[PDB]
Structure formats: structure tokens, C-alpha cells
Amino acid sequence: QSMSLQGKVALVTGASRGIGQAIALELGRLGAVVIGTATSASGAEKIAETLKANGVEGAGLVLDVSSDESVAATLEHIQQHLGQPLIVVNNADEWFDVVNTNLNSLYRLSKAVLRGMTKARWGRIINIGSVVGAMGNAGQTNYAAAKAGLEGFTRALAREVGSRAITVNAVAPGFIDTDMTRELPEAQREALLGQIPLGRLGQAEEIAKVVGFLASDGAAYVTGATVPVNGGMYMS
Amino acid sequence: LYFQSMSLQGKVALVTGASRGIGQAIALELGRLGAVVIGTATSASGAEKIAETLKANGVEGAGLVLDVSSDESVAATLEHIQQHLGQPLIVVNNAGITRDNDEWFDVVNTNLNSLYRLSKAVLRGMTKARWGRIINIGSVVGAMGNAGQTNYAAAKAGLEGFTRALAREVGSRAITVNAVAPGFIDTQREALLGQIPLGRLGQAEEIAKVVGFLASDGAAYVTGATVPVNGGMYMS
Amino acid sequence: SLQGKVALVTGASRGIGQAIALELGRLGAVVIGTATSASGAEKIAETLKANGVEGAGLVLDVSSDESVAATLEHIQQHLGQPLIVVNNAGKDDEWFDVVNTNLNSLYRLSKAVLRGMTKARWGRIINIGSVVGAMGNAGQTNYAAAKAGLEGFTRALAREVGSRAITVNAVAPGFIDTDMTRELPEAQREALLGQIPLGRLGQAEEIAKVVGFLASDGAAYVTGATVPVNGGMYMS
Amino acid sequence: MSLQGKVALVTGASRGIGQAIALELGRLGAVVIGTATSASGAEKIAETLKANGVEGAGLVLDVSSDESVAATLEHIQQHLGQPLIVVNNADEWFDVVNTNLNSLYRLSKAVLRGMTKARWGRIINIGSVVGAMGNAGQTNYAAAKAGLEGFTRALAREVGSRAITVNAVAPGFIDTDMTRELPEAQREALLGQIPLGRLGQAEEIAKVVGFLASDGAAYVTGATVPVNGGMYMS
Ligand SMILES: Clc1ccccc1Nc1ncnc(-n2cccc2)n1
Ligand SMILES: Clc1ccccc1Nc1ncnc(-n2cccc2)n1
Ligand code: NI
């Protein structure tokens, strides 16, 4: 088989809702042992229940990607009980601090999990960009800045780790049906749909399928890529 | 009396330029995923070879003769396919020319005209079925130097812009249009590997896996995208 | 300076083209502006005279090799070789023909004027993209496609002719104050201005000033570039 | 094209591209404050401006320190007026890019008050010159350029409504101190990748910066203008 993730341990941050949950379920369905994380104990319990309800081995844990202690501790804990995670999905005025903080977190987590991947001479790091919602300028500015940061970062880290058969890729979601987007005013939703050639919102499962492919052996020559998953609507 | 459980079961896929290398590998991968595959070549001997290969690999389908530069040949071949096998709802355009057939403008122009010719012909079938996949394969990183870098960048820029525009035109019909941009694919050698983070050439099968994913139902929200498959070496 | 240099500006009878001819003239070039009709050419000649610019208005069909060859010969006969050339002369499914036609015309003209520039070992070719003309969707598709074609073409031609100290650049206008843009409803106008960080439309003179800089000796190391002049609103 | 009546701050103005920018802005009629990280660099800047007939000054600035930035700005307002034109010219890839963007943000954010008050402004960011390299060099260079483009584009959106434009210039291979001293093999290889078949002069970057600082560039914002003789790197 070419799509089996059987025998692998996958860490998926921000797995309690929406895109993160769908990614955990998809990696599990493909046979991985899945560790989903949230920022709170209640989120982590929920993750564990969801995985069990769907017949997936793994666990839910509490993780703050902004803290070196939390990252180090969580990783240790994972190695203790479950093995090295060789698949890692990072899903966890204002634009500069946001992007800066996000990239520092991506770097923190990525750098921590690389030892394990370097040892195993195999790895998959996949970064999930932020969903498209807010309008006028400030939402477009945040969205374009975050995406640009994500592309550059992903491209650079891919170069640094490539010789070790570790691939680093990103997924850039467009307008996806999630908690934030279900709440959005009718006018926003209509405007947005008008910009989308497929004339509909993406499902969270449609992001998860892309992540699952990238995590497979078939994607082994794909690295430094950002795959946009946005129904044909492009926005820089 | 035997139904495959493979993701493209029940579909008919047309793959142009299927007699060698990347095109052959795509035909085999689509077939392995359960599609009925029609591979094309420009000559009767190429087509006969395609048919034998498919048979040797247990794939249902056929090899046919097709000149993507002629409206007659395209119309005729499509009619023939409907006659005997059904509407092809997956189409992979791989048969691009090169300067071996000043040079950058005529190459890119000719290739885009052929992409448009074929795509436009198959759209009626896809429009009726309210479902489709068109995937365009870019050219392999060919010549080493200057005129080679100009041809390569021009072809890739044309491929991206085209793919993005066609995706907009056909999106409302649940037809996705995507592209794959190969880097250095195997079918002084040390210098090259030094420019590639993965430190190796890509296999033709690694392009075929990406095409196979994009043809699936999981890639349904992915459209207008160019997925680079180049081991981390980027050149514009 | 541009003093004593001969500049050919296609589509110079109205708007952006006229503003470019006047700006190049103000910078001291001898300006040949073109139109597709005799009445347009007379108008060009009157405008230049009214503004104290030496030069002429001529009739030129950029889609015809004869017209191009003839017009060039005429220019050499009476005025000298034009070493500055500005190409300005140009529902969801008209994009392919438009872009194709525009690129063939750019190539035709550029290739014709290169012999003169090659002999002088000096040159400036500047390509003006289209304004966001019609709107909604088909207008965004046409615009993005035209711009992508313009960027790739400009970049490739720049590579081909660089060794001869000829620079090839492009200018990508956003929303400029023109006939099409003056005519849309107040709600349209307000929406549009909301998408533009500068909160206003561009003047044609603001395109001309960029062209004038690129034609100068100061821009001699700038080539293959597309300078966007769009008040901060980006749409690909 | 006149920058008469304006005050321009040009960081890293002691050598090469920075010096050429300070001289070009001065030639266009601006009052120019060039900065260096040391007192000797600042003294040199002042002498060069004087030798070339340019009003202004050289001063000491550390773009990585909020105190230095705040102090230098206050100092400029004290003696010369608010600078409405600002040119930012002043394992390893992540810290470099991060630090550079933090410095761009620090300085840009500080000078914006003055520009916001005047409802007019020009911020221009100069990217790094090509080629001090290995593979780690290509990674640093591409990462820095991507950060510069995204940053420039975002800041332009944030400040546009105030008639402040934010742009960038992306140099290719330019004849400078660092590049003259590069191994001859590097230099030859690089020259082979450039369609114009020559190195850029520092003056050729300065001319672009000068144009972008002018009123004629008022509708240009969020742009990164590459100035690289046709050699593009991805
Ligand atoms: Cl805008 C911004 C703010 C902080 C960090 C990055 C960006 N933008 C951006 N755009 C492309 N690449 C990067 N980058 C790459 C490595 C580190 C930052 N950053
Ligand atoms: Cl003809 C050509 C030559 C060199 C580089 C590009 C092109 N054409 C081109 N380039 C980018 N986009 C497009 N495009 C988009 C829709 C149709 C063509 N066409
Ligand atoms: Ni324990």
C-alpha cells in the first residue's frame, strides 16, 4: 500500500474542533496512532473521546505551542508512552504580532520534533494556514500576511531539513465551513461565495484529505510547497 | 464479476503522451487506482505500446492515436472514446512540445493552445456529468543554463496562469483544474543534487501519485493550484 | 535624459497612452504615438503639438506584420530608430483569446523594434497591462489572466535581450480614473474604494510617471520587472 | 521629482547602497540624515554629505533597540524636523529574518506618528544583496526576500488610508564592498546568471529609491521592485 500510515505516530495540534479534528480523524482512518492537542484539559478529554468514538488509537493532550516547557514536556510524555511522532501537523495594528507569534510557535514545535525525525531519517511536517473570514482590509491584511509568512517559513524549513528525507509542506485553506464561518453575516457569506469559482464553502474533510496525502509515501518528493485549498479563490 | 475498491473505480481517464516516462507512470497509477485508462501517443506504434503496457499491468482501457495540435484529431478521438468506453471525466494533459519541435514564445504558445483545445473539447462531457478533473503536467527541468531557464520559467508561468484561469471558468460545474510542476525527474550529476534539498532525483511514480490524488474525491476543493513536485528546488 | 531619443507609444490617443506620450515628451523624447485609425492619429499629432512635443501620430495595427513593418520603416525614414517602445494597445470565458491576442501583438512589435535596439546596443521596452475594466467575476478572471501573461512574457523577453543592454519591463495598473470606471453606480464606487488602501482611484499621469522612470538611464539595471501601480489593491 | 522641503532618514548610510541612496535623495533636494551603528561611521556620513553639498547629518542608531530609536527620532525632531521619508537599509535563517523584520517594524512604527500627523509619507525597505552564500546562503537570501515582500505588502495596507506608501527594493548582484571581496568563482558564476551580463551599480538602486520617494510614485504601494539585471531567484 501507498496511502497506509500504519505504524506511525502523528501529532496534530489544535485538534479539538473543525479542521484540526478532521485532520486527526483522517490520519487515524489512514491507520496512524494520533495524538491530538488542545490548550485546555477539557479540550484534550474531548479529543480522546472523539478518537475512541471513531475507533482511532492515540490520545488527547494539553499543549501550549507558545511555551518551551510545555513543548518539551509534551514531547517527552509522547515518547514515554507512544513512540516518536514522525508526522506533525501544526494547526494551532495586530498583523505583525500575530504572524510573528505564529512563526515562533511553528519553529519551536518543528525544531523540537526534528530530533526524532532526524533519528528515523524520515518525517512529515505539515503547517495549516488560517481560514479566510473577516472582510474589508484588516481581515485581508491579516490573512495575506499570515499566508505569506507561512509560505516563506515552510519553504525555508524545507531546505534546512530536506537531506534527512523530512518533507515540510503547508496547506492554505480558503473559505471553510467552521465555527467562525457559520456565524458570519449573510452579506459577508454572499460576497465571499461570489469570489469562489466552485460557488461553495470547503468542508473541513477536504482540508484533511490533502493533509493525509502529503503525509503519505506518495508525497515524498513534495517539499517546500504550499497547497492552496480554496475552491479557486486566490487572495494576496 | 469483480469490483475494485480503489478511489477512481467507475471512471474513465484520458492521459495524453502516455507512452514514456511521466505519462506512462500516470496511466499506470490511475489504472492502479481503478480507472479505465485511455493513454495516447502521436503514432500507431506508441499507441500499440501503451495498450500492451496497460495489459501487462492488468489495467482496463486502451491506447489511441492523438494529435493534440489538430481539432479534427481531438474531436475524432473523443467521439471514439464515447462510442466504446464512456465519457472521460478525468483528463491529464501531458503531451507538451519543446524547442526541439526565439524559441520560448512559440513553445509556450503552442502548448497553451493544445491545453485549451483538449480541455475545451472534454468539458461538454464533464459539464453534463456535473463532475470533472483536468490536470496539466508541466515540463521537466530540461536544459541546464540560460535559454533553458528562460524556456522553463516561461512554460511554468504560462501553465500556472492558464490553470488558474480555466479553473475560474469551469468551477461552477464542479470541475477542478490543477497543475503539477515537476522538478528534476529520473528516467556534474553531483552539482545538480547539491541544488536539491532532498539530495535526489524524483521518480516518475512520484509525479503520478500527486496526479492520482488530485483526480480523487478528496481533492474536490483543490482548484486553480499548481503543485510543485521538485524535492524542494525552486526556480522562477 | 530621454533627450533626442525616439519613443514609440502604441494606443496613445486616449487615457493612459496619451498620458505616457505626454510624459515621455515632457522628458524630452521625440514621441511617435499610434492609433488604429486615421482620426486617432490626427488627434495624437494635435495633442502633441498643443503640448509642445516634437514627434507625430501614426496609424498602426499591432495585429498585422505588414502594418508593423511599414510603420517602422516610415519612422526610420523620417525620424530615426525608436529605442523606447511602450506597448499600450490591447462572459467568464473570453480570457484565453484576449490574452493570446495581446501577447502575439507584444511579441510582433517587440521583435520588430529589436533590430534597431540591437544595433544601438541600448533599449527600453515597456508593456502596459490592462486596467480592471469590466467587473464582478469574468472581469476579475480576464484581469488576472492578462496580468499573469504580461508578467511571464515580460520576464522571458527580458532574459532573451538582456545581453544587449535592452531592458524589458511592465506596469500593472489597478483602478485608474477612466471611462469604464467613471460610469459605475455609487455603491460600486464605494465598495471599490474600500478594497484600495489609498482610498482613491489612480490618475493616468501616475502610470505615466512610472513609465517615464523606467525609460530613463536610472532604471538601467531594472529588467524583467512588473511594477504594480494600484494603490495597494492586489488581485491575482 | 523634487524632494525639496523634506527630511529623509536613511539607515546604514555609511557604505555602498546606503551611501548612494543618501546622496541621491540629497541630490533630489532632501535634507538627509544618514545613520550608522558607530560614531566613526556617523562622522564619515557627515563628511560625505558635506563633500557632496548635501544638507543634513550623520548620526548613530541601533535599529535593534527601542531606546536608541526613540532617542534618535527625538533628536531629529529637535534639530531638523520630522523625517517623512524613511529608507530602511540596515539555524541561522529564522533568527536573521525575525530580527530584520523586528527592526523594520520598530523603526517604521516609530516614524509613523510624524507621517500620520503630516498625512504624507514614504517608507522604503532595501533588501539584502545577493550572493554571500553557500546553500545556507540561498536559504537565508530567499527567506529574507520573502519576509521583506510580505512585510512590505502588509504594512502598506495598514497605513495606506493616511497617504503613506510603503515599498521595497530587491537588489540582485550589486558592485559593493562585500561583493568585490567574494571568491572569484562565486563572482563568475553569478555574472553567468545575469541577462545584462554585468553587476549593478549602487547608484542604480538609489535611482529607484529616489523615484519611489517622489510624488510621481504616490499610487505605488505594497510593491517590491526587483533591481537585478534580470536574474530572478526562487
Ligand atoms: Cl509580515 C511578517 C511578520 C513576521 C514574520 C514574517 C512575516 N512575513 C513573512 N513573509 C514571508 N516570510 C516570512 N518569514 C520567513 C521566515 C520567517 C519569516 N515572513
Ligand atoms: Cl506566451 C508566454 C510566454 C512566456 C511566459 C508566459 C506566456 N504566456 C503566459 N504567461 C502567463 N500566463 C498566461 N496566460 C494566462 C492565461 C492564458 C495565458 N500566459
Ligand atoms: Ni505518564
Image: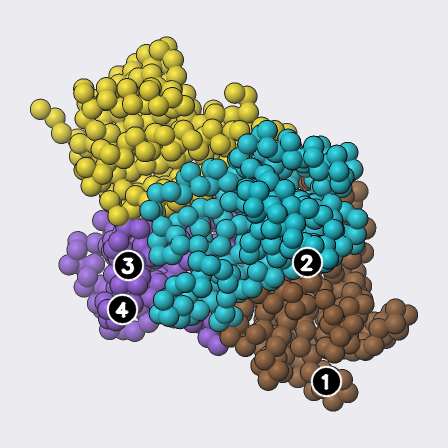
Chain colours: A purple, B yellow, C cyan, D brown
Mark 2 residue type: Ala
Q: Is residue D184 left or right of residue B66?
A: right
Pointer 2 indicates a residue of which chain? Answer: C
* Label 2 packing within 10 angstroms: few (<14), some (14-19), many (20+): few
Per the model, the C-alpha gap separating discs 2 and 1 is 42 Å
Q: Is residue C194 left or right of residue C18?
A: left
Mark 3 residue type: Leu
Q: Is label 2 or label 1 in front?
A: 2
Per the model, the C-alpha gap separating discs 3 and 4 is 10 Å
Mark 1 residue type: Gly
Pointer 3 indicates a residue of which chain? Answer: A
Q: Residue at x 28, y 50 (%)?
A: A198
* Label 1 packing within 10 angstroms: few (<14), some (14-19), many (20+): some
Query: Does any atom of ligand 1 lie closer than 8 Å to the CB of label 4?
Result: no
Per the model, the C-alpha gap separating discs 4 and 2 is 51 Å
Query: Does any atom of ligand 2 lie closer than 8 Å to the CB of label 3?
Result: no
Q: Are marks 3 and 4 in contact (CB under 8 Å)?
A: no
Pointer 1 indicates a residue of which chain? Answer: D
Q: Which residue is mark 1?
A: D81
Q: Is label 3 or label 2 in front?
A: 2
Q: Which residue is mark 2?
A: C50
Q: Residue at x 49, y 32 (%)?
A: B109
Q: Which residue is mark 3?
A: A193
Q: Which residue is mark 4?
A: A187
Q: Describe the element under mark 2 as helix, strand or loop.
A: helix
